Image (cartoon, coloured by chain):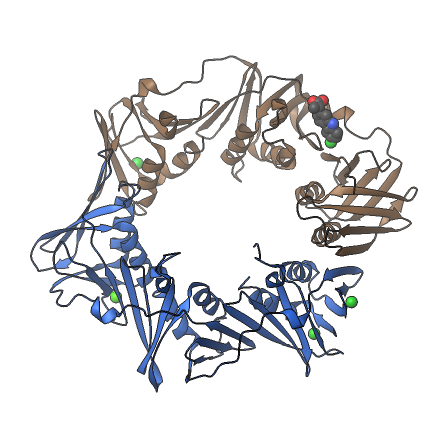
Chain colours: A blue, B brown
Amino acid sequence: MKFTVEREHLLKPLQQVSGPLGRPTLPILGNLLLQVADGTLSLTGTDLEMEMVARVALVQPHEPGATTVPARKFFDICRGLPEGAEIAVQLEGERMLVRSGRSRFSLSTLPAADFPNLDDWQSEVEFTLPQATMKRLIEATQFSMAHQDVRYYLNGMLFETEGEELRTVATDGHRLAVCSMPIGQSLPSHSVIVPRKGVIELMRMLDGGDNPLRVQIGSNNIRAHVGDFIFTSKLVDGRFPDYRRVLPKNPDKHLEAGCDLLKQAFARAAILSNEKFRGVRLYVSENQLKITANNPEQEEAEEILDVTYSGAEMEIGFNVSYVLDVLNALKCENVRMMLTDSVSSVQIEDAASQSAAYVVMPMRL
Amino acid sequence: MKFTVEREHLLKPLQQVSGPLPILGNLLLQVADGTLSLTGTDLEMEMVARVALVQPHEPGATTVPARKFFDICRGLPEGAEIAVQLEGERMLVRSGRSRFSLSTLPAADFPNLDDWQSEVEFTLPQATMKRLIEATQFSMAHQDVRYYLNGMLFETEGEELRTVATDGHRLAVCSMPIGQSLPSHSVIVPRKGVIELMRMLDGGDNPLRVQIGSNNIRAHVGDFIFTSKLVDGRFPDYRRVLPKNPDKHLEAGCDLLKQAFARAAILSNEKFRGVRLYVSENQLKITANNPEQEEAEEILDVTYSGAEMEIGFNVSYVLDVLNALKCENVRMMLTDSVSSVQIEDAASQSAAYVVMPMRL
Ligand SMILES: C[C@H](C(=O)O)c1ccc2c(c1)[nH]c1ccc(Cl)cc12
Ligand SMILES: [Ca+2]
Ligand SMILES: [Cl-]
Ligand SMILES: [Cl-]
Ligand SMILES: [Cl-]
């Protein structure tokens, strides 16, 4: 295996394929697989649950073969060479040599044949969509995923295809986010859970250019192709909660207000909320929202805002971090809150669109 | 105690005094003679900021939680007016229809640095003080048992102010002219003090007044006053640290040398990163290896005079120097494999660096 490649054509691929990898559990999992075949250098990184592959075209002389080498060390070497450096690589059994100018490096190898390899699988649905749509879908919901919950299915994001819609859903059992976007082709009904790190990888591979994303889903795997990057993950083997059953059934009290005005008021009140429980109290009355916070030390914050509200007065408590997370994800002019009573969840949406919806349970407070 | 002031006028003061037990997490607010003073302290140093009060106000003082008060002010909208009124065990803060009640501790409980007397005084541009500290601060010790190294020497000599910092392995010294004849004097400022002083100094052209006592230093710029205790011990004499007669001279591009060190270090021991330098006629070779038997080699074209020699260095020590220099060409002055080396910018003799070698 031999190749020579310009520094900048190797650098972003190395960064991308290292995504799935600080302290590898076993050494080969801290390595990348390098493969030269048919005019292409392929680079692969994996954590045993997902893999990221980059294809790099070779315009300079090369010889086929494969090995694995430490990802961080190889990336750092390539990054540290000067702009435009020509990076020559040659496999020499238990070592891989790297040379550029009068810089020389020898890296320890492990066999390509020992590199873990996600199984082949069969796609059952395939579709294309703009990068921006996938970005919107994930950014709208990712913050509501659980983190290290014993309920493993919640530490992932539901991807659901239905008719001409792709939908993401995330929840940690306290708050839920759901987003639906049209794709312009009719899809079979599929519902799959993508693991935490996989959602991060999908997000990371979106360059923000005009390349479309091609998605394939099977029973136990998902794959996304963007440019010369191919991401594949195993799916989480569980049954996700149904968002339709958690949306409040008849939330007739409707509040409308400016997103940023609400966000900044909640942020200020939060300063004097209980440090652990983060509770704020909302008092809604005719065209007015009062937000109060107090902590065990008896300090107090009060914010009064002009809003549009016609329903009955009520008082309801929320974890202010859950509210702030939603307002931060909406990034819109105006927000609608849909309330029922003091012991029931609130539904929050962009006043302009029902494409995303957020459900937050109240606090006893 | 009552005042009303624009948020804008509080922001910089608040960030400055939030820099240094429970009452130490509070700020002292004092209204007197048409001024609001804000003070923060950690018992070893204090920062005072003053803000003029044109709106009606009433004298008095209290202490409130620093981070809470700062976060409230910062969290209010651009252009906000902030009204404050003391109500016994609470301090009321009002802006528009935002209202806050903070718990207070009495002003009388707020720690004061003992009064002291100035012995040496001079004014210099804050830019000069920044340059002196930036040139040297990275060589201070952190939490050494030799407490006098956990800080920076400030020395006046002739017409110069000099800073010296060392951790026992490497040393930095920088001298700048201040345009007046000074007494010969030296004090050690604690490292946390150095960092707080440095953070008080922005990019402006602004006179800085320094007053040094037996046990304290004070620095005044604009409407900020920083005071710190000094460290009471015997600081090493940099003159005895500088190589006395280096007979080997290496000159190389600063950035080329930096990047070669940085690359080679990738394959050094991760827990203790060093490289070997081999100097010979017109060339520098830098090598590294690790327990996995991985190896790096860098060859540079350099200007060199002297006998061939091999010498090792701690990567971080050399990188810290080259990053501080930010110049075109660097000079290294060597003696032998077991002796310290001096490193300087080829085009400036304002700062010098000494680094002990590392055995590999
Ligand atoms: C503790 C002792 C001292 O004189 O205080 C000390 C302080 C600084 C240094 C040293 C020994 N030995 C050294 C060798 C090299 C350098 Cl750069 C600095 C030092
Ligand atoms: Ca809107
Ligand atoms: Cl190339
Ligand atoms: Cl090579
Ligand atoms: Cl004012």
Residue A71, image x, y percentages: 63, 62
B132 over A346 or under it: above or below: above
In front of the other: A348 or B302? A348
In the image as oriented, which residue stretches furthest toward the left? A312
Q: Is residue A229 left or right of residue B284?
A: left
In front of the other: A341 or A86? A341
B238 over B266 or under it: above or below: above
Residue B1, image x, y percentages: 25, 25
In front of the other: A175 or B31? A175
Q: Quadrant of ligand 1?
A: top right
Residue B346 visible here: no
Q: Is residue A325 left or right of residue B41?
A: left
Q: Residue B128 is drawn in which quadrant?
A: top right
Residue B134, image x, y percentages: 61, 37
B33 over B133 or under it: above or below: above
Residue drawn at x 24%, y 46% is A279
Q: Is residue A363 left or right of residue A164?
A: left
Residue B323, image x, y percentages: 67, 45
Residue drawn at x 27%, y 57% is A174
Q: Residue B107 is drawn in which quadrant?
A: top left
Residue A235 visible here: yes
Q: Residue B244 is drawn in which quadrant?
A: top right
Q: State which quarter of the image contains the C terminus of chain B.
A: top right
